[PDB]
Amino acid sequence: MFRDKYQAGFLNLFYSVGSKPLSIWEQHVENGYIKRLTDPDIRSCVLEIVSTTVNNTYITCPIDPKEELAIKLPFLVLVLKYLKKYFTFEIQVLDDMNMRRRFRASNFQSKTRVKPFVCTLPMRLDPGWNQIQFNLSDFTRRAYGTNYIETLRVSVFANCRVRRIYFSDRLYTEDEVPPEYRLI
Amino acid sequence: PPREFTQFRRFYDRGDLPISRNYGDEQGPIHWKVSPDLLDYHHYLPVFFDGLRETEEPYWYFAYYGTLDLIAQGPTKILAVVPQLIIPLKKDLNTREPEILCRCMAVIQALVKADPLISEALVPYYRQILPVFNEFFLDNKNIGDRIEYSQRKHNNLSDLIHETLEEMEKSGGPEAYINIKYMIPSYQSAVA
Amino acid sequence: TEFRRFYDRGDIPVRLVHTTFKNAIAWSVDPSVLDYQHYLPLFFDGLREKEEPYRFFARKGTWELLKNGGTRVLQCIPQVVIPLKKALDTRDMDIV
Amino acid sequence: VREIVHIQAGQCGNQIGAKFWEVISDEHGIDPTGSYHGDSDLQLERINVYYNEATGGKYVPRAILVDLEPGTMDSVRAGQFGQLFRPDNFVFGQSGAGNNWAKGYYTEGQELCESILDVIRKEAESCDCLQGFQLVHSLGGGTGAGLGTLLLNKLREEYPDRILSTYSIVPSPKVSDTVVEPYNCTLSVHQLVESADEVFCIDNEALYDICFRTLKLTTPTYGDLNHLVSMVMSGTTCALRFPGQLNSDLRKLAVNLVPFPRLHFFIVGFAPLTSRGSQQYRALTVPELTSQLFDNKNMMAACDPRRGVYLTASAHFRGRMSSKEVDEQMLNIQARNTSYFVEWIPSNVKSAICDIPPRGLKMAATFIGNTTAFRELFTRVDSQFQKMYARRAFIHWYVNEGLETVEFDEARSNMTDLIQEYEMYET
Ligand SMILES: Nc1nc2c(ncn2[C@@H]2O[C@H](COP(=O)(O)OP(=O)(O)O)[C@@H](O)[C@H]2O)c(=O)[nH]1
């Protein structure tokens, strides 16, 4: 699904100013909460996820476990607030000869092992709002070497404040974007 | 635990100043009979700290806002009275009602901001204070994707804990974090 | 064929011109900047298609690129022989 | 896809908003405790606009109640839908105003601000699409007017794009309830003009006049007047929640009606209105709706449009009707009264239809218009203010707050400038 729809420019997947921004998103909560609130930081719409055990609390898209996304765009951009706590998220991608491949990055990670079934990345952020961009095509060709194929599933875990999750066809720097597709 | 009798009521019936709520002036919530600078700090402020435990007017309104004004106007002198404030402050926290602790956390946040030396002097007193915080730490509620009103009451007690703990952690210095771990297992440092 | 997958989502840079007289193809990407090592095997795969829209694009793109590319075809021979083998072993009435 | 957070200052405003929630819950079929027990699946198409769901199948409304003394909140909790409001939705001050506009704004406003802003805050990042708040307040009093104007500024600062839709009750010019009122309204107008995107004016004198022209209620109470205001609010926000055949929202209405940034004060009206006994005789049709909407005896504003001319107009319809009949009316009544339409702004009238009418009232309509007749309203309060100001006895009450004497003059100068702007635009 998303297969036959037009996919050019920008294509968002979570943005808290719709009507049920998790209408396509699925939430799993344990030892924590998904709560939606306002920050004095930006005065603009945000969602919060906080939990004691990060692995047991996450959001995944799409809702249907058996069904998958057909988004073509190679760039995934996250605009999130770092809560000075343990954070992780994972992405699923298909490759040229049809093997499912998955990346999961963590801030409490240690190494960058690329054993076949799942790749792991350590990363560090800045306290406040971050604007991480993940070029899936570059990463797939760098790690495994296979070219890029459309993206299957996206999951974000607890202890982070997320306000946008959108895809872009190519890399846009600041101000070559819609005025709200950036940081206030 | 019954309502341990508050000294502030006994000081207020005969001698306390903040009765004045009358304005033809560009002034705030409360007024003083005399300028607070002339007052001593060993007698008035500890009594004011005890008054936050009051539940009915006019006692608690004067005590809460009187504490805020005194801590704002006279931040230099409060360092001497810091040891004497532990006992009345510890009385208020043990009430555990979701209203007194909000006032106490507001005072504490207004207290640590006054001087980094004050917070360094509160490091030995963490063990006397934090157990109430260590109980209420994880009382947030799961609502999913829809709305929080509690913050206009300013009564989401958990969120007050997080900011206030972050405030002692910044001003506490080198040994504040390890003491916090000894009281709060689920806390993780926000030093950077 | 797999060539259906790329064309079905508007990835193959070709379009059809209905100049009434002979159906012809137009390039969304000029042949100069085309990555022959990537696009050439896909055009060879489209020959196995049956219905008209993919069949016409496959023939025109394959013949055009082969007859104008030049020496750039030489490196792509081992990659395009395998789809050519798949096309032949169909034993089809008109794919052969 | 359009979620609105509703704000209520005002002893008047809090009562009006409560009756509005009565109307919405009856329309949607909501138990005054928030449990759905209705009969129409269309009621849940867009219920998220006005409500939240709490875990347990309970719906909580996007309602903010603002006051400075707990008396009104105690009355609201004694109301039918007091349990519908989340208990944290209410805030009240601890030092009353007594309709002193300066006291509420200056001394009480600053303390109130740090508390009040943050539901306006945390509703914003969690109301699923914020394209506008909604505020109902009184202008003659001190608590609603001063605090509402102050919060309107903070709403504009924190939320620039979101539409600040405001509904205000104008001081009654023959007699209104308060008499600090000319001072209060003068100071609130200057704040309202610059920040609020839309301002709607209602007069109690017109409401009583309408009741005795149309309703023939021998002895009405406040409940009827606030119910009519609830009808107007239901008609204004109906297009967002329910289907139709042609619909305009708040931003469309701002686009369609506002020709210039400061000419956005609008009159409001509702049809049909009929006495409880004579409704049987009346055959309710589209021409009957059009005649009632544009008839002067039905305007809920103390300003005769016949003394002025129309700039822009808007009409909305609830229920299933033919568009040809509606637009047949919109041409012929536009041509009938060419003496009231400005020559260089044609297309003054706009049309809209919503599919679901309210209960019992099979066919419904709501009219919002713009006319130069607004100039009479500001003239009356200016005339009353002039000799009151001419002997400064009352401003010393406001000066002791901290308000400068020059503050009254800049509001008066802005008021006169606003009057002049509407005078040139007539020609
Ligand atoms: N229309 C209407 N007006 C009311 C009602 N209750 C109070 N008012 C008006 O509210 C005004 C006084 O408001 P005030 O006590 O100063 O509170 P404020 O609205 O916050 O300024 C008076 O002019 C009353 O006429 C009501 O039920 N309906």
Image: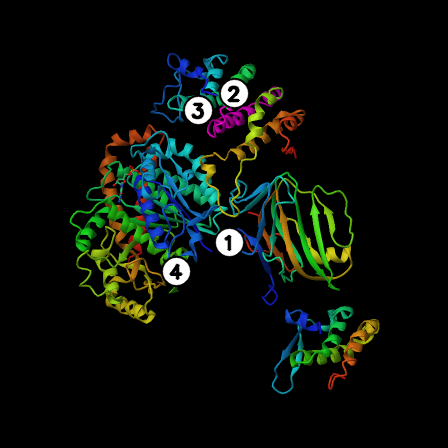
From the image, state whether disc 3 or disc 1 is nearer to you: 1
Name the residue tied to disc 3. B65
Q: Secondary structure at mark 1?
A: loop
Query: For the residue labelled by badge 3, is the local secondary structure a helix, a strand or a loop?
Result: helix
> Of the residues shown, which amino acid type is indicated by label 3?
Tyr
**A2 displayed left or right of D378:** right
Side (left or right) of B111 relative to D154 = right
Circle 4 or circle 2, nearest the eye? 2
| Mark 3: C-beta under 8 Å from nearest atom of ligand 1 | no
Q: Secondary structure at mark 2?
A: helix
Q: Is residue D383 magenta?
A: no
Precedes in sequence: disc 3 or disc 2: 3
Residue neighbourhood size for the residue with mark 1, other residues' Cα within 10 Å, grouped as few (<14), some (14–19), many (≥20): some
Q: Quadrant of ligand 1?
A: top left
Query: For residue D273, which quarter of the picture?
Result: bottom left
| Residue range corresponding to the magenta coloring | B93-122
| Callouts 3 and 1 in the same chain | no
**Residue plotted at (51% across, 23% down):** B94
- Whole-angstrom CA distance, mark 3 to mark 2, is 16 Å
Residue beneath disc 1 = A20
Q: Amino acid at mark 1?
A: Lys
The chain under label 2 reads B
